[PDB]
Structure formats: C-alpha cells, structure tokens
Amino acid sequence: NLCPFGEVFNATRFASVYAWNRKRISNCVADYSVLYNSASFSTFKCYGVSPTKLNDLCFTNVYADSFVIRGDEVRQIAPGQTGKIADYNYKLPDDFTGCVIAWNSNNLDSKVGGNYNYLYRLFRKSNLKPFERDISTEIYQAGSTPCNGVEGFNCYFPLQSYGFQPTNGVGYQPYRVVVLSFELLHAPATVCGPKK
Amino acid sequence: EIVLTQSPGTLSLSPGERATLSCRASQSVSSSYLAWYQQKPGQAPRLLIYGASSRATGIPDRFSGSGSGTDFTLTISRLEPEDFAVYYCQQYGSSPWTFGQGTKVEIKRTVAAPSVFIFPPSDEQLKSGTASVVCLLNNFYPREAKVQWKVDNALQSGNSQESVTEQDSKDSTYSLSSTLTLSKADYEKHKVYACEVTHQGLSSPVTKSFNRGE
Amino acid sequence: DIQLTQSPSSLSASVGDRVTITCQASQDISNYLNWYQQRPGKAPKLLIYDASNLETGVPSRFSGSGSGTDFTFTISSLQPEDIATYYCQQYDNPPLTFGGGTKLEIKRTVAAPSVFIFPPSDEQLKSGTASVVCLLNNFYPREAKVQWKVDNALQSGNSQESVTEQDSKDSTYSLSSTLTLSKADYEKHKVYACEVTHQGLSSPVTKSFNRG
Amino acid sequence: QVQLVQSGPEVKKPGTSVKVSCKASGFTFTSSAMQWVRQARGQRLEWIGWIVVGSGNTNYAQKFQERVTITRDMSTSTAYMELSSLRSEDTAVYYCAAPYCSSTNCYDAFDIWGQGTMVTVSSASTKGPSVFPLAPSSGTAALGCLVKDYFPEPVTVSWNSGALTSGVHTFPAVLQSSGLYSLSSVVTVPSSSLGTQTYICNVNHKPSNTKVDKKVEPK
Amino acid sequence: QVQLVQSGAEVKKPGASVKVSCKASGYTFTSYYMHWVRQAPGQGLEWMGIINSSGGSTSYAQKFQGRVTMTRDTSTSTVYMELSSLRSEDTAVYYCARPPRNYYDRSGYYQRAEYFQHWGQGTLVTVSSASTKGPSVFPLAPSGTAALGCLVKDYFPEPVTVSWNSGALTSGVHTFPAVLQSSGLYSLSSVVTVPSSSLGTQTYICNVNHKPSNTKVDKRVEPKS
Ligand SMILES: *[C@@H]1O[C@H](CO)[C@@H](O)[C@H](O)[C@H]1NC(C)=O
C-alpha cells in the first residue's frame, strides 16, 4: 500500500491553475525519495519540514495539488505572496507545512499556435482564502452596475488563457507545479514514511 | 448602431434662465449607460452626468439629468455665462458607443459696441517683403459685424481674412481680427490705410485709419 | 560587518534612457543582495531580491545581476515615477547591512517658475510677527535665486527656503521662501517684493505688494 | 492627482500611420478601461473604440475597424491608439478617456479625460512661425503679436509666461492661400502702463520645435 | 492585505527610553519574523535586529546590544521595539519590516529569505530637551491660475500633516518640507494652485494635524476683501 505520487507527478495532463487539482492521500506508506533524489525539478522549497526527513515522518493526511502556471509565477506559490495567481487562483496559508515542487513543461504544454486549454482567473472581487478553489465563470462586475450576465463596459469575463508558446524566455513558458501539504490533526497518523 | 439625436441644434438664453436639452435614441438604451458631457472651447469633454441621473464628482447642483428608454433630458437650472459650451450625450451600453451631434448653449447679452484698433505692419515684417495690417474689433455683441478695408479711399476685396473668437466665458462678447495682406511694393505705393466697422451697437460706421510713415 | 559601497551617490538621466547603478560588498555575499526603491518620505519598497529576481508587481523595466562582491541594478526605460533613492542590502551574514544609497533624478525640459507672493495674515500680525511668503511653482532645473527686497533694500539673514522633492509626474520642483519680521519692522515699510532668477526666465521676475 | 496625459501634436503624410499615447496616473490602471474618441474641427465627437486594460480586449467601430489598433503597456501604464492609412479626413483632435478605479471598484462612466492630441495629415511640410509685434499706438490701449506662416496647427500663445491673462484674445488661426497658417493674439491694457510695464508674447510651435519670446514696444 | 501600523511620532529627552509599537493585521502573526530598521533624517538605512513572532527569541545588532529590547504580544499581534539611553544620534524614523518565511531546499539545507516585502509607515522619534508645542495656522490668501495656502508655524517636534478639503483636493498641492527656525521651532507651508474662476464658488479649507500635541486645526482661507 504505497501512496500514489507517480499518478500526480507523471499525469499526462495537468489542471488549469484556477481549477487546480487535488489528490487526497491517506492510509499508506509514502516514499518521497523519488522526489528529493531527482534532478528534474527547478523549484523545490519546503516550509516547516525538510524534504530529506520526509521518509522518517508521519502525518494524518497528505494533499497533492497540481496545476500549470507561468515560470515567472512560480514564486507566488509560497506563503505570504501576492499577485494574480496567489490572490485569484491558488493561495497558500501563512502557516503552511509542505513542499512546493515545479518543473519546466514547455515540451509538454506549449504549442506553436498556442495552448489555450490552460487558463487563469484575471478578475475577482476579493482574494482567495488559503486552499480555496473558485471555478465560476460569472461576468466580473467592475463597477456598481449589475452585469446581467453580459460583457460590456465594466463587465468582463473573469478567466483568461495563457496561450502557451515555445517562447525564448523560460519565464513565459509553462511550468507544472505540485504542492504537497502535510496535515497534522488530533488523530492517528495514516500516511507514514517507510522508516516509520 | 444607435443614433442619438440632440435637440435643439442651438440654444440662446440669458443668464439665470433654465436650459433644457433633449437626447433621443433610435432604440431603447439602459439608463445606467447614458452620459452627458460638457465641452468648452479649446478644452476636452468633461463628464457632467452619468447613469442618466447621477452627477459626476465636483459637478454643481444646477446640472440635472433625467429620462429613460429613448428620451433623456439635461437641465441647467441657474444658467450662467460660463455655461456657454457644446453639450453631448453618449450611450456606452451597446457598441458602437455613439455620440449625439451636440447642442450649442449660448448666452444672451445686451448689445455692446466693439472697440476698434488698427496696427500697421512692423518694420521686421516689412524687411521680409510682406505687409500685414490688422484691424481689431474688441468685446462686441451680437456676433454679426462688418469690416471693410480701404486703401487710399479704395475699397479692398479678396485680400483680407477675418477671425472671430468664441463667446467669452465672463462677459459673453465676441472679438474679431481682420488681416489685410499686401506686398512690400503694393503697401508702399499707398498712404492711408483704414478699416471701417459697421455693427448694431454703432449709430454710424466707425473708421480707424493710419498714414503710412506717420 | 559587511560594507556595501553604492555608486554613484547620485545621478540624473532623461526619460527613456537606461540607468545602471552598482553595489560592491567588502566580502563574498553570494547572491543574497536585494534592491529597494525609496520614494521621498515613504518606506523603502522592494524591487529586486536575491540580486536578480523581480519582486511581484514590479514593472519589467527593472533588473539586477551579480554574485560574490559586485552587483548591478538597471532600469531599462527610465520613467517619471522612478524618481527615488535606491539602496542595496545584503543578508549573507548578520548583521544585515544596507548600501549608502543612490539618488536618481530625471532630466526634463527647462520650465520657468510661476511666482506668487503672500502678505502676512492680520491674525498673525496680532501675534507681533509678520511672515511674507514667496512661492515658485513647477520649475526646472532645481537651481533658482530668490531675493527679498523691502523698500528696494536687499534682505539677507531673515528668510528661509524650502524646496519640494522632484514631482513624480512632471519632474518639476517647487520652492517656498519665508521672510520673517517683527510687526514693528513690518509696519515701517511699504513695498515688499521677491525677485526670482531662473534658467527658464530671460529676465528676473519680481512679484511685490504694498503693505497698505 | 488622477490624470490621463496624451502625446504632443503630430504631422503625418497621407497613407502613413500615427500612434497616440495616453499615460495614466493616480488610479488603478490594471482595473480600468480606455475609450478613444476623435473630434473634427468644429464638429461632433466621434467614438473610435475601447480597450479593457487587464485583458487587452478591444472593440472598434466598423468605420475604424480595419485601420485602428488599440493596445496598452502596463509596465508604463500607457495605452496607445494607432491609426493607419491616414487620409485628410483624419485631421482631428484625438482624446482618450478612462474611468477612475480603486483597488476594489471602478467609476461607472468615463470621468477621466486626456487633454487631446492634434493630428494633421497633409502633404505639406513643417514650417516654423514668424512672430511680429502689433505695437500699441501713440484710457485703454491694445497691443499684441502676429504669428504668421506656420504649418501645421497648433501653436500656443501666452503673455508674460502666463502672468498676464485678463483682456487677452488669441484668435483662431486662418489658412492662407499659401497653405500656411496665420494667427493674432492681442490684449488690452490700461493707457498708463505702456511706458512702465513690459509685455512679451511667448509662442510655441511643437511640430517645428520652435519657441519664441517677442517683446512688444510702443513706437 | 498585510498591514503593519506603527505608533505615532514622539519626542523624548536624552537619556530616556522610547517604545515603538507595530501592529500586524491581515496574516497569521506568529508565522513570520519581524525586523527593525531605522533611518536618520537624510541618512541611510540601519538594521537593528530581529524577533521571532512565535517564541519571542531575538537577535540584535552589536551597536544596539544592551540598549534595545524587542518584544511581541501575540494576543494583540503587536511587536515592540524599546530603545534606552537615548542620544541625539537616535533621532530617526523607525520601521518594522517583514520578510517572507525561510524554507528548506531539496538537500535539506535551511535557506533564509531576509528581503523585506512589507513595511510599516515608520515612526519619527526626536531626541531633544525641547518641549512639545502645537502650531499656529495662518492663511495665505489668494490673488488663469491663482494660488492659496496655509502657513503652519511654531511647532515641535516634527511632523505635521496637511490635507486640503478633508482630502478632496490633491491636485496641484505642494506641502513643503519644514524648516527649523532660529527659535528651535518648526514651520512649513502647504500651497495649492486653483483656477481663478473657482475663487468665488469653491471653499478652500486646510486641515492640519500635529499629533505629538493633539492639535487639529481646520482653517478656511478666502480671498482678501
Ligand atoms: C515519472 O517518470 C519518470 C520516467 O519514467 C521516473 O523516472 C520518475 O520516477 C516518475 N516519477 C514518479 C513520482 O514516479
């Protein structure tokens, strides 16, 4: 009963960031060595835990959230950050305990004519709470006049596509991101490293 | 398109009266997407009313808006001489965001006689081989004036150009400048240059003249 | 401690040009060097962290580079609102230290000042002091000469000047000169004038009033 | 200070393109939108089209649809309007406008307007103005300046660098048969100030980059 | 939505002590370190020290060791910096600054991230024997474009704040830096240019706030008659 991390990391397609995917991992033995012993990752930052200790630790549940963003947006997947992604698409808590892992996926998610399957939320009335997911497509009301589901002056569609192309600067290229959350509740631990 | 028709084309009223401007649409337009702008001469449009009844920030209470459907009304209650302008209605709820043709609000005034001045060409312009003689009619109402150039008591035609300013924002008068252009040779052949002004505020036409070289 | 030497201390350049300022550390500080922009009277705002990473929300015209001892900070297209003082800061080793700063100014076209003069208020006259105020509005360059004249007598020693920082929009300055007298001395004279000499004026401009 | 500031006047040969800029200050540019309007001389306002700042989506009137491109550059908070295939009917003043926007809300109308940009399309070249004094004669007198033989519009005329504004009349320019423009700016002053007060007219023609300060003396 | 709001400007006698507060809102207070940075007027930035908002551990710069105490109260989400034995060199604007969290990289190494993404508005602390004095506000009456203003005179210490029409008027407003008069009292002027036509229609009032003396003055300025 090993935890299925390869399903998350090696999935053929990833979610739009506004509709980020979440895999809930319970009741299993987790071998994180396949992660921290790999050299394919361009971002690997853990908060509240060192990755080299993960095989010796136990948690109530583990969460793996996955999505695609721009490379120059990966810095927003961190506690306390702001920006379009952190404010409107995927927000981490200040007291986050977990890892943020990102790799360049230009070879997979870019198209010469643009990949318009990947979207992000551009307009929102307020910032997202931590771990909140909003997939609504209501017309954004920029003013005080109700929009009645119609685009116009101060009435804007809230989603926008990345349109990923094989650009020359890596900061514009698409990056796949997995965020691992390690949950500790007042309950028996169900996800444990092989050493425990 | 949505055609916005304003009424009337021009509007002459004395200060203190109430001006009523109408904007009519070829089809219905939402009230919260119709606006009134005031444009003064040499100036950008300025938002007067929005949402057909809301006053923009800093807009005086004498400006009011109302209406619905295919008819909207802008009212200036305590009309003031500084309110001479062109007033435009714009709909911005359906593309294209059409404008009305505008309504010209002008101020009525007591008849005023122009002050007439004559300026001979300068020596600096003389050295260039062209002479310009300028006749100035200052602060007169109504606009209709007549300026005739006479050179050695000979009426000129086809060599002068007039220019009229807009109605003043304070005294609601007009000003006119007439330039007579001649060559150096033609200018130096003659002696007395005069401009004769005929206007309602003058009992008889007033001639202002100078003698070249004096 | 690690000392951060910034260069140049100050500089000026026109809108659109490229600006490159430098920061040198006494020892090796890897890439743990940050760049802040401090607009006049406000708190420093982070623009670049770890010597090359653009802080979220910062326009792309800013960039930085370095690792070790020498670091550079660059503005590509100079913009009116870039008027500020720029500081580098290391955190490779405690205590954290900042650079001396680099004040960036914007060159623009010469603009003449608008000169206004203000007699003392009657309310202040009750207190037994008179302040005459001369205001120069929206001029460039910064240098200007304000001369107080009382009944045509040139005054020195009894006035003070105050200049605004460069405006973030039009890149101009403003200046105020205050001439302070006792009420007794103020009533003794009639003509109070301030005379302004500036690059944007062909001849000096005088604004005056009579005490009556 | 909430403002929209446009670029200076432009002269373009027929068939070329013009790009007018509009820089925003004092409000949340990222939440706003910008509409572009054109006004012909002594004519009505003509809507050109608008852009949403955050997305860059544009909407143009059918007449300008094939010829105008509206963009924005958020690193400088500046929107742009480019008009191509310039014909003489494009000679006009071009305005940008935007609603004021905070971090949360936007104004429900176009309440911020730019000063406008005068664009002249013609085959004629750019000619600087010649300035001549209209000297006062020898209880109120009148003096002025004549700004002659320049192209194209506009020119700006002030008196004493803006200190003198009462009694001034800067007449609208007239087009001479030579194809150049002529204008007169006069002002009336009391008859006791000719021998004491000095009067200087300050004329600027941006298209030719010519600034002139001419003193007017009584002969 | 992170907010750091610091206590008001104060004057303190030499040899005394000052306690500056910094109230944090919009985030989980105990998740971040808080640093203190000071700026002497017209000088550069100086780091004072760091406090762990969770457990209250501190580390101070050498030149302030033995003289500065950093505390935190998690109940009110507030951080305090206390500086004792104040000298003239301690006259400065004091800032609380917040960097992001530290993290571990793939190799298990602890990585620090001490770049300050958030700042308080700062607190001016003036070290002087002079007593606090509230200002007097006098009108600078007006005359195209006209100009009017308010003269804020004979106050101590800095600063004062001047708004116009309760914040409604911002365009064309210039509030000049104060000047230290020969009497040891500060003085500044706030001016604004307006259209001339507006002189007879719009009312102009300047709002002056000298917090260190609890002085609030609203002064209407009208053309002289
Ligand atoms: C994903 O696939 C690669 C190549 O087959 C493999 O090396 C890697 O271990 C896989 N990742 C996981 C988490 O199983």
Image: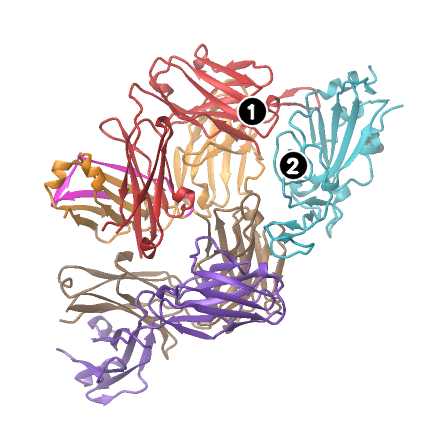
Chain colours: A cyan, B purple, C orange, D brown, E red
Question: Which quadrant of the figure contains the N terminus of chain B?
Answer: bottom right
Magenta span covers which residues? C143-169
Relative depth, front residue between C202 and E125: E125
Q: Give the side of residue B12 with respect to residue A66, left or right.
A: left
Asked whether B22 falls inside the magenta stretch, the response is no
Q: Chain of mark 1?
A: E
Q: Which element carries disc 1, helix, strand or loop? A: loop
Question: Which numbered disc covers residue E171?
Answer: none
Image x and y of residue D206, in percent:
38, 61
- Amino acid tagged 2: Ala
Look at discs 1 and 2 and give the one toward the viewer. 2
- Amino acid tagged 1: Glu
Q: Quadrant of residue A132?
A: top right
Question: What residue is shown with label 2?
Answer: A86
Q: Give the side of residue D178 with respect to residue E97, left or right.
A: left
Q: Which element carries disc 2, helix, strand or loop? A: helix
Vertical position of residue A91 compared to residue B40: above or below: above
Vertical position of residue D130 compared to residue D197: above or below: below
Asked whether C159 falls inside the magenta stretch, the response is yes
